[PDB]
Each structure stands twice: as structure tokens, then as C-alpha cells.
Amino acid sequence: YAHSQSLDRLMNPLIDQYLYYLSRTQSTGGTAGTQQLLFSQAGPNNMSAQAKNWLPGPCYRQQRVSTTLSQNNNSNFAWTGATKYHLNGRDSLVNPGVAMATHK
Amino acid sequence: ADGVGSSSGNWHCDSTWLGDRVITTSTRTWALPTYNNHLYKQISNGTSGGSTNDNTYFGYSTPWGYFDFNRFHCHFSPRDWQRLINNNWGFRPKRLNFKLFNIQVKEVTQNEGTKTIANNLTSTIQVFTDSEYQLPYVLGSAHQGCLPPFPADVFMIPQYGYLTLNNGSQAVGRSSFYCLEYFPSQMLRTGNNFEFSYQFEDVPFHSSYAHSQSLDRLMNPLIDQYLYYLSRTQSTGGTAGTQQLLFSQAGPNNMSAQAKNWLPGPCYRQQRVSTTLSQNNNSNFAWTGATKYHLNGRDSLVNPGVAMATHKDDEERFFPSSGVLMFGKQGAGKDNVDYSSVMLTSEEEIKTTNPVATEQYGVVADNLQQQNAAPIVGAVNSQGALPGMVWQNRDVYLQGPIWAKIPHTDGNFHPSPLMGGFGLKHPPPQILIKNTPVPADPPTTFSQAKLASFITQYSTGQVSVEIEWELQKENSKRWNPEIQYTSNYYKSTNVDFAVNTDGTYSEPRPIGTRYLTRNL
Amino acid sequence: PLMGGFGLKHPPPQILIKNTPVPADPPTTFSQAKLASFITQYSTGQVSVEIEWELQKENSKRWNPEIQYTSNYYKSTNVDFAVNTDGTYSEPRPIGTRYLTRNL
């Protein structure tokens, strides 16, 4: 199955949170930039700033290859630019690897 | 039997402390309006407006409302909280019981400027509990709309909505749309009442205590170790620096060099912010210098984050930017409210087992040394979990969330909520409620279109929720006195956790659960 | 008690009563603040209280007559312990409980 909700979006779009985050560390709009700690409640406007009970799965990066040939760099990076793991003096290509979304 | 003139239930608020069980019951009075004029509505936000790419969403806002009892202070009085956190190591819920009763549905109309309200005795409401977990479970995000802390407050029931997969403001093919009327619900008139019971799945006791020993100090201060470490790689004191491998046994003199069976919990660094303004850098780094996680092309601030000590010894002024739970004081603004209005919680008690939020996890070597090449050590800012690694979970508060739903997924690691709480796979089923729409007079000639004119209507009533708890009694041979939660002995303009002159209830400070001690 | 009475360690439990608040129409858009607008409302009814008493009968060999509480024999504008023309009840004098005699 595929999830019908992303992990970060489990929130209610209608209601604000009672929790606060650090929104602004600087005086805004004034002739001076005197640092001041301002707090705010996250809500439908900023959902990137809300607090969340969970995190995404673990990440082990891979190199990005485009099917379009003109975009990829001109060289052979298949083995060299690869993501490998070093066990007992032998570099082993990491294949297929940890489950990670193919592309955004 | 029941009718328009006989009440559906009785008021219950009380706490029964019996042995290891504490049974807390509560009751409030609510009012459920008519949201969206009895309509589901698509809601979305795109990046084509002023919004950025991280803030986009797509979802629906339903006419239904929902009950949220998911904060602790809904269920505990500050004195019942003091009996809990002072006298017990751990507590977990066992079962709950829930009731709606005394349902008053009222029609309200407008004639010129005057307003008038009247009972509608035939009207109904609709209530179902989603006990198969077949809906977006929107509790546990720490939204407003919970029962008030104070039993004499009347609260408005929040609107139910949910978000679904999007691309920009647009929706993708996997986007689900749910019609809440497509479930069986129970329709209640003013004589009817509602009830259900629920039984929590086994969960580890929330550990409420601070360790009396740091993780690195578990050693005996008196006796040396039979193990050796590499103390000195160079000839000492001689006219030459000829490298020589010298070994030593660690002991009371050097305890930083001893061998240890365990490691601190995992570290994901936060940015350090000082309450003193002169120390912080002059710029706005709140969002930019933040610690974020990148999921599907959207940067999401990491809040509150993994449990990590707020600050080290003798620094109370520094706190991690996104790290600490932040509660607002009574009557505080929603946006850009000054520091003195929020209440910053702090984790002092987990400094023993857990690393400080604003500092590195440790140091590793970056290179293979040679006689030519000097050894180089890098910093470990983010460290996942390794074997032989122990940590403490984040602390619950009187104001904070009780539980969370563990997402249904192939795998999880330590499924305990990051805000603190009890991670549940089958959490308490969310309860949905709505005013059954009553049409205004239709035309006398048939029309295919749906009826767009309704009677302005809302309902009120009484709700009760009773949770049985399981306590772990504190059994300890410590000689000296503990640290207890005590109210301020000195005089004040008004009592804390009590009404002011104007009747406004207020909670002056966040109250964590760990005052007791154990041995690490 | 120094005012006179029966000092009780567990006196009759005080009875408290209140009108359950009924809210005026809330707004159609959710708000965190408590509901400040109520329906003006009051209640009425009937209350009954019935007390059983224990008497100590007077048993005395005194020859001559006691002193009794007697209403004024002489005429008056209106009866004592009864309504006046306007319906106002009134109690003309305080009445103590000690008219009987005993031997000290």
C-alpha cells in the first residue's frame, strides 16, 4: 500500500498548536537590528515550523543520475562516484541499498 | 426512562487514589457550532502565492467536530499532579471511560438587530468513535481545543479537518477523500446519552525520576581497574621525543580514561540560543540557522527533536533553538510574542544519560596517522544509535500531550513520541460529533439542487472522561531527602494555579514529572 | 459555641447549588478562548427540611407555679408574630428558651 498522508503533514489543517517555536531572533523593521527573542504558535500558515512526534527513516545517500544524457556529467563516475562500504579492505558497492524514495 | 425533563447523567470530577491505581474522572461543558454550513471543503495552499514550498498543503475541512482530552491537565489537578510526581516513579494509563450527556440543541435566529435563542427539542446530533482507525488520526499533533485545565471553563469544540498527499497546491492520484457521514454514527436527541469504554494496550511506565548517577561515573571510586589503556605514545622528559608506547591502568586519578560498558544516547545537534540578548549573534538565524530535516523537497524544522539535555552544568541561559517544549503564559499572543510570555521547559534530569542538545556528541579520528602525518580528529554532530547505547525519553508535563499514534509502518525505532507521551499503536479512538443539519423551508415546486438554506443551530452538553492509571510505587533506600515539587512559600499577589480577580485561571509554570531519583 | 447552639464535630453537611452554565451561540470559526457569552438564566423550586428532636420532659415537685411565656393579654394594633396590613411578617421580641426552673 502507499500512505495517503505524508509524515510531516499528520497535523490538523484547521487548528493552531498550543506549542511555541522560536520565530524571530532579531528586531524586525526597526532602524536597528537589536536581537530580541520572539516566539509564535505554528499553524496553517507555517506548517514547516510545527512540532511533530516522529521523524523520517534513516538516510544513506546515493549519487544522482539523470536518464537525460545531456544533464549528467561527462566522465565515468559509475564506480568512482559510487556509494560504497568498506569491509576488510574491500570496497563493496552498496546495492540496492537502504529503502529510500527514488526521486522527489 | 429518559425524556426531555430528566437529566442524562451526573457531574463527576474526582480522583480516587487507591493503592497503585489512581482513577481520575473529569467533566466539562461544551458547545458545538455549525462549521462550514454543513459542508466538506477542499482546502489547499500553494507556492504560487506568498507561501513558500515548505508550507504547501492539500486537504479537506469537514463540518464535524471532535473531542480532544489528550493533555494531562485535562485529567489532573495541580494537587493531584503533585501527589503523582512526588510519590511515584512511573505511571501508565490502563483503561478509560467516556460519556456524553445532557444534550441541549438550540436554534438561533436574527430579526433586524435583535438576537433570540430557543430550544429545538426534536433536533439531534451525530456521534461516532473511530475504533477501526480508518480515518486520518489527527490527535497527537498538540493542537488547541482540549478540555480546559479548569473544571469551571466552557470550551468550544474544534473543527475536524485533514491533510492529504499533495504536489504544490494540487493533489496527486493517491490523495484520499473521506466522507465522515459514510460511517455508522449514533444520533442523539436531548433525552439520549452516549458512552464508550476503551482499554490501553500494554505500555512501558513513563519513567518519572532523575538518575542519581551519571553514565560515565558508574565506576567504584576506590579501586583501580585491571584493564590498561594507551596513556603515552611519546618518550617523556627526555632530550628526544622518540615515540614509545606506554600503558597504564585507569583509576581514581583518571576516570575519563576508564573503560565503560555503555554509551550515551544518540545526538542530533541543535543551535544554541542564549536568553541574554547581548550574547546572541545579531541577525535573524531562527529559521536559517535552524536544524531541519529534508523530506520530499520540503525542509521541516525539527521540533522538539530527540530528547537531549537542554544545557550543561552552570549554564541556564542557553537553550537549543528548536529543542525545548515552549508553553505560553495565560493570555499570550499567537505571533511574535515576547520572550517573557512563553514558558520554556528544560531537561536537567537527563544530562546523566543523554548528551547536551547544543553540543557535539563526541570526537572521532578523521585519518590514518603516519610518522609524516599528524592525527586528525573530527566532530560527530549527528549520531544515530549504536549497540550498547542507553538514553532517557523526553519528560511529560502537566500541560503537554498524553500520547500519540505510532504510525502504521514496516518498521520503527523506539516508537516513543518525540513530544513526550505514550506511543500507542491503537490509541484512544477519536470521537467525532456534528449537528445534524435541519433544512429551512424548501420551495413548493420541486428542484434538483441540494438544499442550501439551513436553520442556524448549535448544541451544548456535558462530557465526562475517566482514566484508570497504573502507578509504580517508589521504593528506595536513599538516606537523605529527595527533591519535591513545592509551591512558593513566600507571599504573592495571588495564589498560583488559581483564579485572579477577573476569574481568569492561570498556570504559572510548566511542571515536569521527574523529581524522584534512582540509581542509573 | 459562643453564640449559643449545638457544637458539632460533623455538623450537617453544607448543601451547594448552581445553575449549570448554558452558552450563547459560539462563533462559526474555532477559538481557543473560553466562552464568555452565556444565556441569562435562573431557577426556582421547593425545598423541605425535616428535623427530629429529642426532648427531656420536665419532672419537678415544685409546688408553686412556674413562669411561662405568654403573649400580651392587652389589646394591640395588630397581632404579634403575624402579618401587618401590608403583608410584612414581623417578630416583635427575641424569645429565649429558659422559663422552667431546676435546683442548682
Image (cartoon, grey):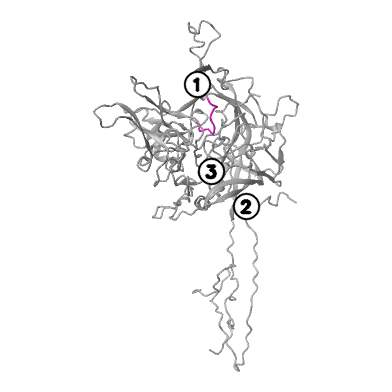
Please give the name of the residue rendered at 32% of the width and 34% of the height, measured from the top-left corner.
B279
- How many numbered marks does the figure carry? 3
Asked which quadrant contains residue B403, the reply is: top right
For label 2, the crowd category at 10 Å Cα-Cα, with few meaning under 14, some 14 to 19 and many 20 or more, is few
* Residue A53 in magenta stretch: yes
Between disc 3 and disc 1, the foreground one is: 1
Which of the labelled discs sits on residue A88, or is there none?
1
Which of the labelled discs sits on residue B11, or is there none?
2
The kind of residue on which mark 2 rests is Trp
Q: Main secondary structure of the magenta part?
A: loop
Q: What stretch is highlighted in magenta?
A: A50-58
Report the residue marked by disc 3: C34
Chain that bears disc 3: C
Which residue is situated farthest in the left direction here?
B239
**Circle 2 SS class:** loop
* Label 3 to label 1: alpha-carbon separation: 66 Å
The kind of residue on which mark 1 rests is Asn
* Residue B226 in magenta stretch: no
For label 1, the crowd category at 10 Å Cα-Cα, with few meaning under 14, some 14 to 19 and many 20 or more, is few
Instruction: Residue B392: tell me if it is visible.
Output: yes
